Length: 9
Length: 35
Image (cartoon, rainbow over all chains, first blue to last red; front, top):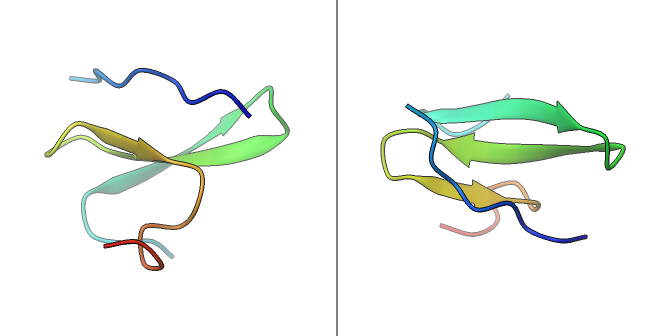
């Protein structure tokens, strides 16, 4: 559970 | 095996979360099921 905020460069 | 662009990363959730770098998105369910 608990979705991670996404920002992967 | 996962959609072109999506990375599979194994989190401490005992869970591999699906993560696309080109659209900036994350999923718990395989993006093939949710396009």
